[PDB]
Every structure is written in structure tokens, then in C-alpha cells.
Length: 258
Ligand SMILES: CC(=O)/C(=C/c1ccccc1)C(=O)Nc1ccc(S(N)(=O)=O)cc1
Ligand SMILES: [Cl-]
Ligand SMILES: [Zn+2]
Image (cartoon, rainbow, N blue to C red; front, side, top):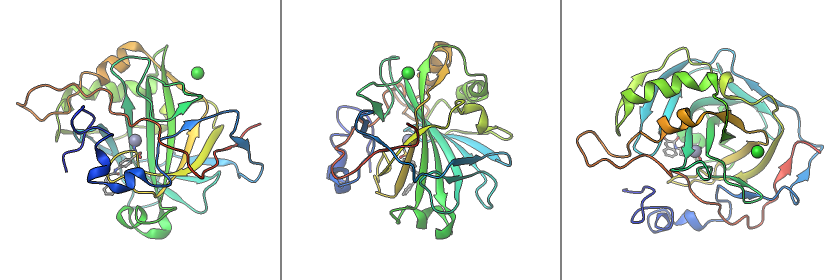
């Protein structure tokens, strides 16, 4: 497959190789704050990242992934809408060419400069590859980024990007604490959806935090110096690696907060 975010291979083309692109529970979606309903049935969200073991950072030609050791319950997401235990495997971002676009989810049609995805898999399915074949296999924690003051906890990520400029490059990325990327509040919206890239599998419980984190213009400018292309190839800046909002269809977005 040769999918990407250009005119010629971008989200409007994905359905030809990945027909689920036009499915009943695609992501992202616009979060209409006036139709999402507070759900008193939601349990408190539990983000347990104290024992998180980061390993590596990889430019995959679509975004960059910070990968974790998920061979045991070291960094887990529980509670909120989730049944059981979901293990952190990686995080990555989606971002724009300019500060007015870049997020995948929108909030009353507002686009943020970027969106962080912390990807977790349901440990009752034993491995990530099995989990993505299940409707409750993954929980992705989505966090909006706006441009304002620097996020200190992001700087170690920003500073290694020079070493993974092009597709296929990786770097050692140990001892990175993903707690440094969370906002103060864990208030969230939740809905059933999909991976937002091919293969667009409908296996995700989305948990999207209401409170954005602030990052500096300098921090997001360094995201925009990455390349989609491999070393030696014509430079295509890694920008606008976001899928637009997809039809909500027969889904309800629930709020954790009044
Ligand atoms: C190795 C790798 O990158 C992956 C492989 C994979 C995933 C599923 C099936 C086969 C391979 C993967 O995890 N894909 C992915 C993760 C989160 C999101 S998203 N934007 O919905 O959070 C989008 C894409
Ligand atoms: Cl805001
Ligand atoms: Zn993502």
C-alpha cells in the first residue's frame, strides 16, 4: 500500500484499498459539545504511567512513534468507559502546516494545531495484532495541542527529531515519561471508532480529553521539519498528517463531565 496525506494518496483515496474507510464507526469525528451527553455511568479514568518503559522513537513515513515495552502491565489505561486493562504500546501526533489545523478530532468544528494519540491494547486479547481484530481491542487517549507556552515534558521528543528526519529512521528513546504530556484535567469525551490511518480498523474506544496542552511555536515548528520521504529522496515535509472528521452515523459521544 502507498497511502499518505498528499492530493494523490490522501484520505479521499484510502477507500479504494481500505473499503472500511466508508464504514459505520470511522474516526476521527467532530465533537459537537452541545449534543454530547454527560454519562453518570462512566467510572473515573485511571492513567497509570508510573512504570512506563519507553524504548525507541521511529519515523514511519506517516508520523513518528514513541514505542513502549508492553511485554507486561507497566503503563496502563483503565476506568472511564473501559472494561479491564489496556496496555500502552506507543504514542504519536498528528499536526498541521499552520497552527490553525492539524488535529483529527475537532470540537464544535474547531481544529487544534496538533493531536497526541496514546495507543493502548486490551490485555484480554494477549497481543496487539489480536486486539485490533476486536471491536473493544484498543483505547486511544487523544490530547489536543494548542500553540502558546512551551510544554517542558515535550522537549525531549522535540530534541531527538533531528536524528529521525526521514522515513525508516529510529533512535534510542529510553526513560521518557509520558505523564509529562497530560493536561491537569482528565475530563473527556468518549465514542466508539477506528484507527484514523489505514488499515482504518473499527477496534478503538476513543477517549478525547477536553483540556488541550499548550506547546510553543518553536516546538511545533520542529515537528514540521520532519520528512515523509526516506533519506536521499526529494524532501516532502511531514505536515498535515491528519484525517478529517468522518460521519458520526449511529453513534453517541458521551461526556465524563457536566
Ligand atoms: C506499527 C503501527 O504503526 C501500527 C500497525 C498496525 C495497526 C493495525 C493493524 C496492522 C498494523 C499501528 O499501531 N497503527 C496505528 C495505531 C494507531 C492509530 S490512531 N491514529 O488511530 O491512533 C493509527 C494507526
Ligand atoms: Cl481551547
Ligand atoms: Zn493517531
